[PDB]
Length: 140
Length: 48
Image 1 (cartoon, rainbow over the protein chains, first blue to last red):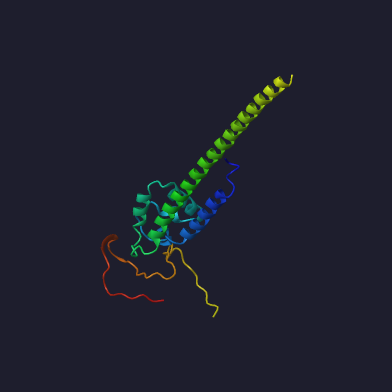
Image 2: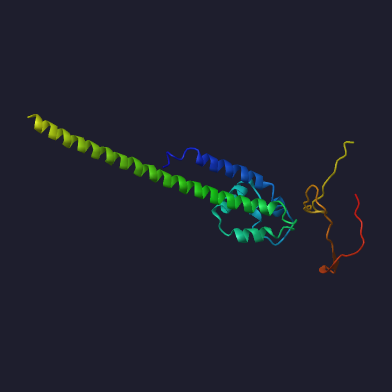
């Protein structure tokens, strides 16, 4: 399986890279604001913090609460930012989870396929062996 | 030209932090014998 992980892994990490670096300077006014009462401020502060928080969005834990904690930013009619992060989390999570489970069950499929063709070839060889045993017996 | 500025920490303190292209107005408070009593709401000006 991990040998078969060739291109999908770098596709996953490069989508992570592009989406994280896009979302760095999207909720910039979340961490860079003068609001005293906030507790998810550090999530969107640094580039490494951006990687960690978009990984959190990828894992999809408390995305509701993350969105309400970013709602303390002045709502600019949600025209670009909230739809961007929601689309990113949903698309990335479902597309990558689905693609990995699909390719893993495909790996199981061809494992069983090569196993079954091996037993079929063994059965064909056994039939040929038994037929040649009849041929040899009649040849004596 | 080659104008310079000498920051005085004791008189001023740590300056506030603001960013580029942000509509900002300062908030100031009235102090009577060293206790916060009421925020300012008057007409006021700032200058350099």
